[PDB]
Amino acid sequence: HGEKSQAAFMRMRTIHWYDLSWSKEKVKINETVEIKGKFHVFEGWPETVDEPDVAFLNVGMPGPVFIRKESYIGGQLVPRSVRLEIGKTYDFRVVLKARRPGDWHVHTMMNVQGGGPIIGPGKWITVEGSMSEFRNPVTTLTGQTVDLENYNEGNTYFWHAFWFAIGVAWIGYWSRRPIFIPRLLMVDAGRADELVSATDRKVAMGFLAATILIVVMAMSSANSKYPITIPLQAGTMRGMKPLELPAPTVSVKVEDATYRVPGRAMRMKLTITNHGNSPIRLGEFYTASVRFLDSDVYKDTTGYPEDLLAEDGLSVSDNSPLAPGETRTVDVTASDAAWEVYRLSDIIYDPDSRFAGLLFFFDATGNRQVVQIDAPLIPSFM
Amino acid sequence: VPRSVRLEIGKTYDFRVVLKARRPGDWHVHTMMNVQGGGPIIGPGKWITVEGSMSEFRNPVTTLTGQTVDLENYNEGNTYFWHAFWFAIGVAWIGYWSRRPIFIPRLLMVDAGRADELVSATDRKVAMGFLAATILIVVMAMSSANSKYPITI
Amino acid sequence: HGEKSQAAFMRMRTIHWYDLSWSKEKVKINETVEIKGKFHVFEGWPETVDEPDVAFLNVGMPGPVFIRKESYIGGQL
Amino acid sequence: EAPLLDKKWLTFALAIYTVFYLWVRWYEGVYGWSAGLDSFAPEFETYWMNFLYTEIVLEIVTASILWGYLWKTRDRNLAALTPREELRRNFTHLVWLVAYAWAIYWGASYFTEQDGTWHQTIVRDTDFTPSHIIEFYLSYPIYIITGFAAFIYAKTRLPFFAKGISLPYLVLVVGPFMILPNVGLNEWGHTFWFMEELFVAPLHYGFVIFGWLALAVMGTLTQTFYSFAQGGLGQSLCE
Amino acid sequence: SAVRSHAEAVQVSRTIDWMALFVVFFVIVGSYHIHAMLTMGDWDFWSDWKDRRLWVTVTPIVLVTFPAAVQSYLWERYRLPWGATVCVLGLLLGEWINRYFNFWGWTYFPINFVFPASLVPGAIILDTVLMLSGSYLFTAIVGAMGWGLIFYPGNWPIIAPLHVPVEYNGMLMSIADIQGYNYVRTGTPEYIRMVEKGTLRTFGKDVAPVSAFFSAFMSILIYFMWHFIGRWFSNERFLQS
Amino acid sequence: GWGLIFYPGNWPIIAPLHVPVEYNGMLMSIADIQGYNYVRTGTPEYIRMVEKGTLRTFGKDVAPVSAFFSAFMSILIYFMWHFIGRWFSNERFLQS
Ligand SMILES: CCCCCCC/C=C/CCCCCCCC(=O)OC[C@H](COP(=O)(O)OCCN)OC(=O)CCCCCCCCCCCCCCC
Ligand SMILES: CCCCCCC/C=C/CCCCCCCC(=O)OC[C@H](COP(=O)(O)OCCN)OC(=O)CCCCCCCCCCCCCCC
Ligand SMILES: CCCCCCC/C=C/CCCCCCCC(=O)OC[C@H](COP(=O)(O)OCCN)OC(=O)CCCCCCCCCCCCCCC
Ligand SMILES: CCCCCCC/C=C\CCCCCCCC(=O)OC[C@H](COP(=O)(O)OCCN)OC(=O)CCCCCCCCCCCCCCC
Ligand SMILES: CCCCCCC/C=C\CCCCCCCC(=O)OC[C@H](COP(=O)(O)OCCN)OC(=O)CCCCCCCCCCCCCCC
Ligand SMILES: CCCCCCC/C=C\CCCCCCCC(=O)OC[C@H](COP(=O)(O)OCCN)OC(=O)CCCCCCCCCCCCCCC
Ligand SMILES: CCCCCCC/C=C\CCCCCCCC(=O)OC[C@H](COP(=O)(O)OCCN)OC(=O)CCCCCCCCCCCCCCC
Ligand SMILES: CCCCCCC/C=C\CCCCCCCC(=O)OC[C@H](COP(=O)(O)OCCN)OC(=O)CCCCCCCCCCCCCCC
Ligand SMILES: CCCCCCC/C=C\CCCCCCCC(=O)OC[C@H](COP(=O)(O)OCCN)OC(=O)CCCCCCCCCCCCCCC
Ligand SMILES: CCCCCCC/C=C\CCCCCCCC(=O)OC[C@H](COP(=O)(O)OCCN)OC(=O)CCCCCCCCCCCCCCC
Ligand SMILES: CCCCCCC/C=C\CCCCCCCC(=O)OC[C@H](COP(=O)(O)OCCN)OC(=O)CCCCCCCCCCCCCCC
Ligand SMILES: CCCCCCC/C=C\CCCCCCCC(=O)OC[C@H](COP(=O)(O)OCCN)OC(=O)CCCCCCCCCCCCCCC
Ligand SMILES: CCCCCCC/C=C\CCCCCCCC(=O)OC[C@H](COP(=O)(O)OCCN)OC(=O)CCCCCCCCCCCCCCC
Ligand SMILES: [Cu+2]
Ligand SMILES: [Cu+2]
Ligand SMILES: [Cu+2]
Ligand SMILES: [Cu+2]
Ligand SMILES: [Cu+2]
């Protein structure tokens, strides 16, 4: 939730999430779900979004209904912010543990500093069980195993209640006497010195000394109880390993790209050159989490969110085997209610009417090439 | 490249610029790269002579709504009309109060404590009418502009 | 002097100085000493240190006990 | 010979706010998850936009009626006010101040940090989030209405406050009101200036500044005490 | 007369005392809570934001604001030395109510991950210094020094168990760090947390004391300014327009 | 009112200048084409402080949010400049 309201061109021109898998659709409490996939950083990064020099891989959900057990970018655990390069592709994996029952829309997201949220496709996952069964065991380097759900709760309650009680007692010591009107009149009359006695001064001195001594003793006792402590671990982790992918033996030029403004579709003229890899055929156009597929060339079998999957939303004028070398100019039409449901038609309000997306080409043997396209998008009103 | 672009250090780029003559005379024309946080980078300048009359210059542009306009005079009359209308409204508002003594007698009356005599019920009604008319005219003008141009970006 | 008090990871993760040579160990006044070597910039540069877009090669000593006659990075003064 | 302090009115002043805000919290819990997450959906419309429209209309009607009734029934001749009746009116104004303080706690403290929580657990999508609907457009107008009513009652019933416009009272009453227009800055702060959900960002310093104006209460309190004491209570108490 | 006897006057005064205490307490709760959260609430919400540099520095400086003004009013007009204590207690009450009923009751963030910082010792020090010395300059200097310095030692017994090192998936992590990692804050990524990350000019185990002393000095300055701010806020002026 | 009425008052003038045009394959505004064609040598394109879209920009709320923010800051600036002018209206005489 939160993507439909984001500018259409910003969603089109930031990060592209390609083949994704979810290990389970329905999980029990304390069971783990794995979300893996690839994300590509668009070369034409918008200028109002800072470069992903400081980026964090996040899980979009209405709260800690899951707990993120681990997250890996390129096989490396990433508990901190990371640095990503423009134009590179990265594998990502996220292992989550179920905490609260219910149906949850879970998304993979990249939070970018100086940019904001970049939400990926969301999937509905059902958690069955009771929240009381959730456990979060962690073993420390000191040899102690604790449960993070209730660890250190009683100590915090005790100390906060103790200090609150001390403050309440300090206020109530003075609250046993007339408070506001008689004291104000006495101060106005010049009898302020009569409002504080020697016993009050002794009580204040005792309160101050007891507070300081208790703080010192509590710090000493806490140090004795936990002689091994480390500061909070923070920093930006550089040197993320990107994917070394086969360059596309397929070249695609966008002649024109238009959308009818009333409109639930997008149309584009494309010149495609096959540089080998056998006769190929376009099977899918990915724009903003929406996948328009050509049923005759490719069929999704990964449980891609159906609200974002158009099984026959790709209409190519001529989708015949493009013999290696053939340069065919084709008119592709990406049509689906998701265009209007995911407010991609709101590119009419955007201060930049340019789109970007991914095209997937398959040969007879099923090998897939990914081609990256970007162009300006012209609205049609006649 | 109608917008600002990003260039890399140490790379070479082709550039092309097509210009249309507008005013007669001899003009020193240079190609330049304006760099943000740097300033102007002027290239070699060439003298070009333009012969003719400026009145013959036309700038036709065809919109996506099917209308062909000339950018030299497009929307000029509408801007003049609206600015003159609002200026006239302001002038009328000032001149309504300007028919009476302005500075010295009013200052003396305010100093004497007779300020409440300087504004009458008719003045209050006129001010209310001015405010209501201004708001209503603004709303109606916005609605009419939206109706005339339903497609804007 | 001044490195022992610097954070250990910052010292480990910034610049590595490898094979170094000193021309002389004992010098007279007005005599010259040459210090050559190689330095490698770590790929995982710490985020709290700005990238070495503006860097200066300096000599650490308690003052002008020496005068830096010249300094070359990659053969360039 | 009615009692000086009307316990029924004070009990009502506390209980109406308590019950209404408990019901509001229950509604937020029940419908904040099923309908409040997605803003471009029909259930979100019928469960939160209708709430916003109804609360705005009811706030306008209630503010108009209450302020007009308080200003219409003002004491034209306050010179004949007996000291006992003046003390009773002072107690009623103190009940009004109690109600204003309770509303201020409910608005500026509870729902503001609830809004902070909501923004830290989800991705912001619109300016009319259920948290924003409850906080900016329900609790803030409610405490503004209560403060305006308390100020009007003090000016129209207490001779101490009827001789002019009390500057500390005006600051304490109008200052927090400026928190409501400042919401626009907040929106302009989140949509354009700051790309991150940081609660300590300068775009929220407006709130902070106007919160400082609530400190004017101290000055107001002093005046209130004098309004309590000038009628002869102070002379008897000093004995 | 307004009252018929001295005992009736005493009872009426006690009732006014209770009602005015309610009013002052909850107006202070509202204003101080909104100021405190919108000035330093990101460090106060999460246990993995409670670092040695930014939290320790920032919190006392911004939280010394209201106690200074409330002391300047209460001690001067009523000789009531509990202004700082009442401000801290109201802020703590509001924060705890929100944490229990909203942070945990609504979004189910564990309480050990979302708890406020202890503030009573600093308020007690300030109040006792003001009461014993009776002068606002000495109170400012010494009490603000104590308020800044006692913040971190007072909170150490609470956060100490959360700093036990853990080898989490091959990386060294803190218990608070693991708490922040596991419990996902969708609107609060990791890069936002203003915590110390180490500098090439950071010296040998002096982060927390330096932060505490800087906080104490700025607390002196802010107390001095907010004393006069509250003095202005306590004016009994009437306008005619 | 002063903050809120600024943009509706100017909309009848600038509305004809926002008709979309397909200029050389790119979507442009009439005002954008005016800025492009008529060369400002001292005013490059990157200087214009105009909205370019943010990842936190929501569903068609730019102009109303800007108007309300302008109105609030107008309240503040009016309040301060009232006293500024009150000081500027002083009838004081100096002897040195
Ligand atoms: C006249 C009373 C004295 C005056 C002071 C007010 C005290 C009143 C407290 C009400 C207690 C009942 C709360 C349970 C609601 C009971 C209630 O409304 O329960 C339903 C919701 C849950 O609904 P849901 O979300 O659909 O459920 C799914 C997820 N839970 O829970 C709650 O609302 C409970 C949590 C919040 C309760 C508010 C806290 C209590 C208010 C204290 C005010 C501060 C007063 C300070 C005085 C020192
Ligand atoms: C919290 C921010 C503080 C605002 C500044 C303090 C008020 C101004 C003081 C100096 C000028 C007025 C005279 C003394 C005050 C009190 C005051 O305004 O008295 C009425 C006087 C007229 O009285 P007088 O017998 O003729 O002689 C002057 C009184 N000293 O009005 C004025 O002088 C002009 C209007 C007053 C200023 C507007 C109200 C201020 C309240 C805050 C407005 C809302 C902003 C905050 C929202 C977030
Ligand atoms: C527009 C900027 C405002 C400047 C500040 C206002 C002027 C100063 C006021 C307080 C001190 C003077 C007394 C009252 C004023 C008027 C003034 O200067 O009167 C003469 C007094 C001597 O008179 P007096 O009967 O002995 O008692 C004091 C009068 N209240 O001079 C002074 O007190 C010192 C010299 C005055 C200041 C210099 C002139 C200020 C004009 C602006 C200078 C140029 C800067 C702007 C250029 C861009
Ligand atoms: C949450 C836990 C709550 C803790 C409650 C602590 C109790 C607080 C205050 C007690 C007020 C008694 C005042 C009696 C003066 C009542 C008083 O003033 O009595 C006259 C005495 C006469 O004493 P004297 O013998 O003639 O002279 C002194 C040597 N003999 O004067 C005094 O000066 C007596 C001073 C006694 C002050 C005691 C207050 C100390 C309180 C510290 C509390 C520690 C906190 C708890 C630790 C875990
Ligand atoms: C650029 C275009 C310029 C527009 C010029 C507009 C004219 C402006 C002002 C006219 C001043 C007349 C004042 C008469 C009071 C002169 C006046 O006060 O006369 C006594 C009447 C008595 O009227 P009555 O019948 O006894 O009571 C009312 C119901 N019968 O009192 C009033 O209160 C009369 C109020 C009349 C005020 C008329 C002003 C409205 C002006 C709006 C102009 C709209 C703008 C143009 C639209 C395109
Ligand atoms: C059933 C619970 C207890 C009784 C309920 C009454 C309140 C509780 C205690 C005090 C009175 C007890 C006995 C009263 C008997 C009768 C009764 O209901 O009296 C209260 C008022 C009368 O107010 P009063 O004349 O000042 O005299 C009060 C002193 N007895 O009744 C009314 O009908 C209201 C008065 C008119 C003002 C209406 C306000 C505007 C209403 C519109 C909505 C406002 C905005 C809404 C929020 C946005
Ligand atoms: C009139 C109201 C003014 C504000 C006063 C109340 C405090 C409010 C905000 C600042 C508190 C710090 C926490 C950040 C929340 C306010 C906030 O959101 O700060 C963001 C920055 C970090 O992000 P950023 O990308 O840097 O953005 C800059 C926007 N300020 O925090 C920072 O604190 C860093 C910014 C620089 C300011 C440093 C803090 C001040 C240091 C002390 C000097 C000031 C004088 C102190 C008194 C002696
Ligand atoms: C004042 C009454 C006398 C009581 C003693 C006073 C405080 C304690 C010791 C005094 C000796 C000084 C050396 C400190 C022990 C020195 C000490 O214990 O330093 C610990 C760490 C150093 O850790 P490390 O390197 O692993 O240890 C090896 C050091 N070679 O430094 C710090 O904590 C830094 C000092 C704290 C920052 C404050 C500096 C003072 C700035 C001046 C303003 C504050 C003064 C207030 C003015 C009124
Ligand atoms: C300066 C005035 C002299 C009196 C105060 C003593 C000055 C020195 C230190 C106090 C500052 C707080 C502690 C941090 C220092 C600076 C300091 O010493 O920091 C190291 C550790 C913190 O290190 P870490 O990496 O977080 O690991 C935890 C290990 N404890 O704190 C300490 O060792 C605490 C030192 C002293 C604690 C007692 C505080 C009591 C004194 C302050 C109140 C004074 C008010 C007087 C009332 C009139
Ligand atoms: C962060 C820095 C510390 C904070 C600054 C305040 C500390 C102490 C003194 C400095 C300024 C306040 C002193 C009072 C003025 C000085 C003061 O107390 O009154 C001046 C007069 C009083 O009004 P009057 O009777 O009508 O005028 C005739 C003289 N009595 O104010 C005026 O004339 C109007 C201006 C008053 C504005 C003061 C407002 C105080 C600031 C509130 C804002 C929040 C705090 C911001 C700081 C973060
Ligand atoms: C006040 C008297 C009553 C008259 C009505 C008041 C104004 C109109 C409607 C009220 C209902 C609220 C919902 C708005 C319609 C709501 C509305 O029309 O929103 C349009 C766009 C949204 O465009 P979109 O997403 O394509 O549309 C689908 C929305 N799910 O939002 C906006 O324009 C944003 C709102 C403007 C910013 C102001 C917010 C308010 C901030 C508080 C301070 C200002 C208040 C002043 C305090 C005194
Ligand atoms: C807030 C106080 C209530 C009274 C005002 C109504 C509040 C709502 C909107 C008014 C702000 C200006 C319009 C932009 C909103 C925000 C808003 O609705 O913006 C959308 C469009 C602008 O969109 P765009 O992308 O530029 O495309 C042009 C399409 N029109 O404006 C509107 O739809 C205009 C809405 C209302 C216009 C009438 C203005 C009259 C009201 C303001 C004056 C009030 C003064 C009262 C005197 C006492
Ligand atoms: C952007 C924020 C809003 C602008 C700030 C101003 C708003 C209202 C009040 C705040 C300050 C002005 C109040 C007048 C002082 C307060 C004032 O009106 O007079 C103070 C005395 C008058 O001179 P005097 O008779 O000699 O002194 C004895 C007292 N009557 O000034 C002085 O003594 C000298 C200092 C006066 C300086 C005030 C200049 C006003 C500022 C002009 C600069 C331009 C505006 C900058 C803001 C952007
Ligand atoms: Cu979702
Ligand atoms: Cu891509
Ligand atoms: Cu050395
Ligand atoms: Cu190296
Ligand atoms: Cu905000």
Image (spheres, rainbow, N blue to C red):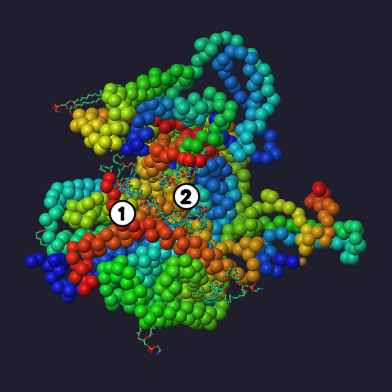
Q: Residue type at mark 2: give it.
A: Met
Observer-nearest of C7 and A52: C7
Q: Is residue A70 left or right of residue D33?
A: right
The chain to which mark 1 is attached is E
Q: Residues within 10 Å of mark 1 (few under 14, many from 20)?
A: some
Label 1: element kind: loop
* Mark drawn on residue E237: 1
Classify A345 as above or below F19: below
Q: Nearer the viewer, mark 1 or mark 2?
A: 1
Q: Is mark 1 within 8 Å of ligand 2?
A: yes
Residue at which label 2 appears = D195
- Residue at 46%, 40% in the rendered image: F94
* Labels 1 and 2 within one chain: no
Q: Residues within 10 Å of mark 2 (few under 14, many from 20)?
A: many
* Residue B126 coordinates in the image, percent (x, y): 23, 29
* Residue E211 coordinates in the image, percent (x, y): 55, 66
Q: Is mark 2 within 8 Å of ligand 7?
A: no
Residue A100 appears in the picture as rendered: no
Q: Residue type at mark 1: give it.
A: Arg
Classify B37 as above or below D61: above
